[PDB]
Length: 226
Length: 232
Ligand SMILES: OC[C@H]1O[C@H](O[C@H]2[C@@H](O)[C@H](O)[C@@H](CO)O[C@@H]2O)[C@@H](O)[C@@H](O)[C@@H]1O
Ligand SMILES: OC[C@H]1O[C@H](O[C@H]2[C@@H](O)[C@H](O)[C@@H](CO)O[C@@H]2O)[C@@H](O)[C@@H](O)[C@@H]1O
Image (tube, rainbow over all chains, first blue to last red; front, side):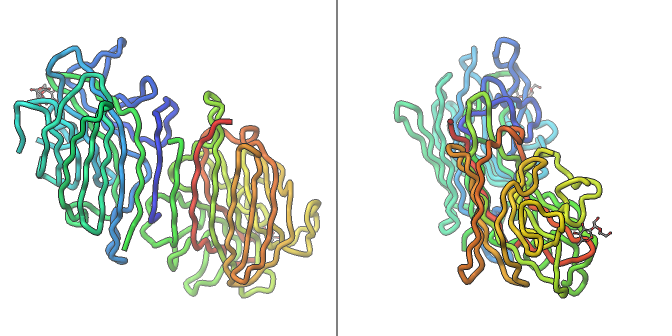
């Protein structure tokens, strides 16, 4: 299809179109990307991701078309620690993507110690190591562009990621319920790093430091344009 | 997802989200549900179907919600014969649905000699028709094991594309079918149906077609679909 869209106001346990990888699973009508014990508390050394089952036609060489897409989602991070880690990321990658061997901890279950575009929200220590940051990743280049961010335990962060094929601008806008806002954008020709068909989803991980990475909602739309 | 939408203005050969069953396959930027030879001509004894890969959440008991959906598509039938057969159908069924053994010919690859809702466009002659004039093609609505719970006379036009819009409103439970040729000739058939009484919560949507002794192409040219859960 030239156009595809789907919306998850919440994530009930009765899932059918999500490819769960690692420790990712549904709990409390939300996707708990990283493992949690019987009390719902985050544990160390855990990685998990999800991908929507239907593939997205990101661009088409024959028709010289590239897709305009938007991804809106909400998540919250909680931890008994004061330095919860490591982070959650929205990513786009080849359809058969799997958690790379040894990509736990700071590699967020996305990179091995390949083809992909990701927007990561890192809370652990191209950016000020002293504080959290939002980063845009392109292929093997992590944080080609970043912006300072603030972690707020248990507070949902609403995010909107948009891609305009005409300008090739990948825009990211994130806000907390009080209006605090973060934004970062970067020019990227999706045709130079990703195949025509891809899958979209989220990934998260925790090494020695931990926190829950709870994806609360997610909506997405994509349409090929001339 | 409570909502899902997708659109195929055409069907290029590099498909990823379609589940091809039987002889169904992509040829000339369209889905050829039934088999065709090297010259584009239809052959006898063939059945084929397609389903969109992502499952559709039709209803949810826990929230007392039912989906409002619409399916728009166009197809064309072509045959060197004077009586092409048998027909093409849009259908909704359990996710693991497969072609029933012996469902060729007049069974369209949908019924065995179950749980489903379908809108079939038949061109075959069945001297046992009890809800439509057998001497002429018909469009019929199928609910579970009841084929053609309601029908309307239709005309077969070789090689001409028929545009169809199928809509379901959970508030009224009306399943509306409107089909038109490029000249505006219109066919309408509608029926009340509580999808909750015939289909599971999650389903797959798609098309099916078959040719027995008589044959014709069943070319699906375009297809768009949208569904959203609503309280109720
Ligand atoms: O082997 C334990 C642990 O090692 C690695 O995690 C490290 C680092 O990547 C993380 O940022 C921090 C904070 O969580 O913890 C470690 O220092 C990863 O290989 C991880 O998968 C693993 O659990
Ligand atoms: O083996 C021949 C053919 O038989 C059956 O088709 C019959 C009937 O269902 C069709 O409506 C008419 C016209 O196409 O042809 C036969 O009479 C099916 O079993 C079919 O699969 C098979 O090829």
